[PDB]
Image 1 (cartoon, chains in turn orange, yellow):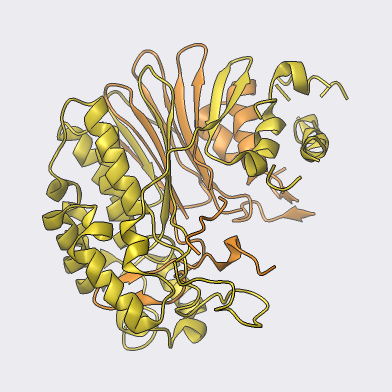
Image 2: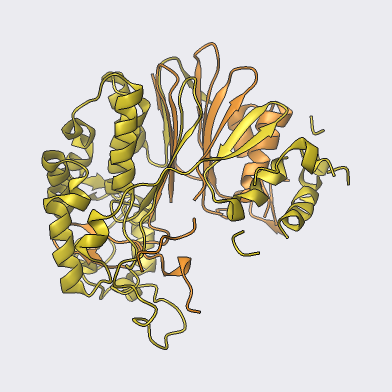
Length: 149
Length: 305
């Protein structure tokens, strides 16, 4: 599962999730396409054309004029609590809000897991400020990259 | 420390995908077209976690208006009937029978782009949006370590699946991290999308090539399933809080619990995790089937616990 954010010069902001739900999906590649196909048998039970019932891209607009896109990959509803309460509620800087340890039960950086557990997730974010300055943040728990001009 | 810029910004799980979005911006493209180029770049570079063979989800916030959501996830195939999975106690995880729902992302790209032509007054050539994705397929990617690890740690189980070894293995093992890894097949696919158009995946030559492949494989999906498929446009689940509005793409059954947590909203250090107590009282608020905007401060203040 990948999360991606983009904000352009006019302030259009995009938050995106793309996935095959499990590693390599079904294993099955479609001949002469290179496409490994997703495997969503879990979105259904046993007592056609039926759609599944699901992933959560996120975005926020703030009273002071900030727009913000974020997203967590792996882990998950507690990661969003953390980033919301840290960044929005508590004024913690964006990059620090994503880095500070999290909980499902807790990261050793405070039952108590390693100082950086892949089970607390990978979160990214962009905040656009009314002065037009653009802020991207990456999760130290992975190898993400923020690229801006 | 935080990277700050003045014009545009892309955050991605792989630096090559971030730069593919970034180039489109610098070339005058919109954030959406930059996102589409990335969706294709991150498909070549992290193929084990995502790609053209899965689903996609957009939340788009225009400069002034309401947010726009894109549920680009596919439905089960027309051959995927309750009978076809006999006395099996679940749907298999691997094999042609697990590949039973349609792949949506590409429909998300086609829909977002039509949105980005309505919002922008312009649009770049599709052949430009896929250019980086194509070249990284023909000419290769730096094998990520997680692609190597995922492939090794699933090698014994997926070793025999149709197309697996020919496409993901090197000398029959997992490719070495830091090595150049090609996808000559995926490039022909991406080159077809560029000549024929993104929607040809469901309604053009590539859709028909995908149909035969499904037949030969025994997959419960038909050409009708592809042609009949559009990205959906549901409404975002919206949370009003003291500092503003926050959106999540989720149906009311799955996303009520998460958004209610935040609606918490007098918090300005260990109390911070405990005040988790809100999550306890939140699942309670959910408790028919998958059964709405109650998430009001007039409704969550009883919190007061």
